[PDB]
């Protein structure tokens, strides 16, 4: 409908796949080469389905900060025959608050879904499903089961992936440029 939805759509059309694990279907953001991200609660194993194709997992790393606190991001390298467009230059370098964000989801259940979530707070600590979690972003939208792995963007920035909600608020794990240096 406007420039926020335009940037979100451009990311969804080239940099997402549908990932299936034993714990469900997730929106999965591809970042560069064969490297993608997914919430750690997806429990990635040795094999994953990517757009309903059986795919070997070459590496999976559940990120934690240097306090050894959960970040809820898993970085996955896929045994896929095709690279993602490199979008690392759209990742923030530092922890920050944002205005006018969009949460975008693409699954069997929720295809071509875009949600204007508004203002995003650098919330920090969250007890997420019983697990102490850092670098959480918060937005005042009643997000639901099926939106985990959804991409959070502003115009020109890919800032996080949706990891949970409390019925009134939604929560994303930050994406930082430093996670994807090579």
Image: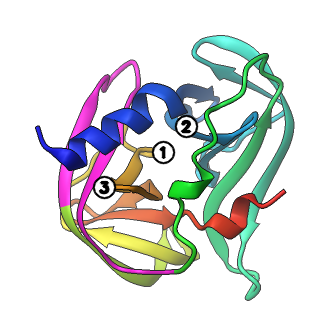
Decide if residue 69 is in sight here. yes
Residue 86 falls in image quadrant: top right
Q: Nearer the viewer, residue 42 or 155?
A: 155
| Residue drawn at point x = 64 percent, y = 30 percent | 21
Residue under label 3:
155
Range drawn in magenta: 95-117
Local secondary structure at mark 2? strand
Q: Residue furthest bottom?
A: 67
Q: Nearer the viewer, residue 172 or 36?
A: 36
| Residue drawn at point x = 75 percent, y = 36 percent | 33
Local secondary structure at mark 1? loop
- Asked if residue 12 is among those painted magenta in the image, a careful observer would answer no
Residues at marks 2 and 3, CA–CA distance in whole angstroms: 20 Å
Drawn side of residue 81 relative to residue 96, left or right: right
Mark 1–mark 2 contact, CB under 8 Å?
yes
| Residue drawn at point x = 57 percent, y = 46 percent | 87
Residue 71 falls in image quadrant: bottom right
The mark that comes first in sequence, 1 or 2, is: 2
Q: Nearer the viewer, residue 47 or 139?
A: 139
Residue 134 falls in image quadrant: bottom right
Local secondary structure at mark 3? loop
Image coordinates of residue 133 in percent, x first then y, are 56, 75
Image coordinates of residue 46 in percent, x first then y, are 85, 32
Crowding at label 2, few (<14), some or many (≥20) Cα neighbours within 10 Å? many
Drawn side of residue 58 relative to residue 42, left or right: right
- The mark found on residue 149 in the picture is 1
Residue under label 2:
28
């Amino acid at each position: 409908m406007g420039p926020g939805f335009d940037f979100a759509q451009a990311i969804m059309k080239k940099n997402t796949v549908i990932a299936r694990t034993e714990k469900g279907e997730f929106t999965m953001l591809g970042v560069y080469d064969r490297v993608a991200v997914i919430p750690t609660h997806a429990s990635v194993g040795e094999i994953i389905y990517i757009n309903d194709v059986e795919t070997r997992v070459l590496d999976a790393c559940a990120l934690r900060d240097l306090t050894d606190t959960n970040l809820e991001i898993t970085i996955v390298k896929l045994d896929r025959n095709q690279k993602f467009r490199d979008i690392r230059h759209f990742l923030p370098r530092c922890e920050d608050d944002y205005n006018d964000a969009v949460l975008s989801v693409h699954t069997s259940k929720f295809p071509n879904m875009y949600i204007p979530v508004g203002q995003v707070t650098n919330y920090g600590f969250l007890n997420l499903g019983g697990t102490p979690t850092h670098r959480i972003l918060m937005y005042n939208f009643p997000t639901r089961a099926g939106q985990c792995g959804g991409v959070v963007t502003t115009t020109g920035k890919v800032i996080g992936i949706h990891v949970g909600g409390n019925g009134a608020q939604g929560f994303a794990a930050m994406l930082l440029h430093s996670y994807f240096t090579d």
